[PDB]
Length: 127
Length: 127
Ligand code: HEC
Ligand code: HEC
Image (cartoon, rainbow over all chains, first blue to last red; front, side):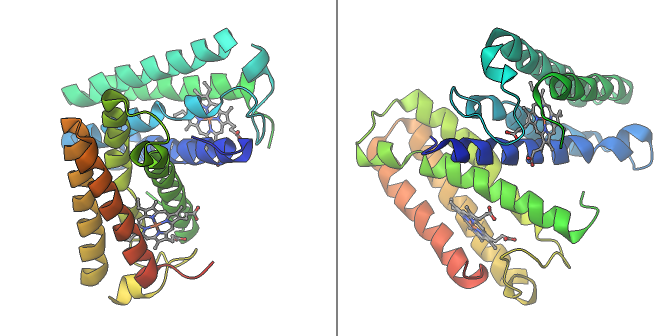
């Protein structure tokens, strides 16, 4: 869907920006600093689930650019493992949110965050 | 979920960027220049549906900025009518996509596009 590589870059950066907001806005809830409304969080994690599937298709071959490391394309199977693992961590968060289980939510949230960081450590250039 | 107005601006611009991609990538399909796979389009319009609900919450009061016109906030009921109407046009597109009906899809796509433009004409500053 991208006329030039720059369009892919813009897409993925936007997708990741939205993910970051949908993930990060729950931080006060998991910390107890904001109240836990099970329905609010269920709906939000549904949005996060949708969004968390989107960036990967915008790292198609030849879409080098932005702060993407070239290892994304050298190493296809390893990058795919990291995104698929990340999406599976999102599944655990969805399960927690759907159950209305705050303890499972906290645990899953931590694991998701670790997965974001593991990918960045391997595949995102320093700012 | 926004620490400063700039964060709201960044969010909505990203949401609208993703909408534009999910909408616009169907143009060749509705024109017949690319093949119509009913399942592909159904899935894509589901993503568009999710995305099309997101920008509006990021025009909360005091989040002036970007290319948003101030009339968004003077005139709340009129802006809300335009976004809700737009989302209802997305419902028609969803119905068409879910039915696998290409003629309804074409018609709905046109109406959606007109709705994007009607909002821009009233509420988005010139580049
Ligand atoms: C690889 C499997 C990743 C996972 C999982 C997550 N992120 Fe990431 N992120 C990744 C890359 C390769 C990049 C660079 C993209 C580019 O082309 O520049 C990013 C970037 C971000 C950004 C910055 C986006 C921008 O505005 O330019 C953000 C805010 C971000 N990532 C957040 C984020 C969060 C919160 C994640 C888990 C919920 C997450 N990322 C996972 C690669 C990967
Ligand atoms: C009002 C009810 C709108 C509807 C419906 C649509 N758009 Fe829009 N758009 C609107 C505003 C007020 C702005 C400015 C946002 C800001 O703070 O700057 C925009 C902007 C866009 C953009 C640019 C985003 C960016 O990268 O800065 C795009 C690509 C865009 N809009 C596309 C778009 C499409 C394709 C729409 C229908 C499917 C659509 N918009 C509807 C207001 C409104």
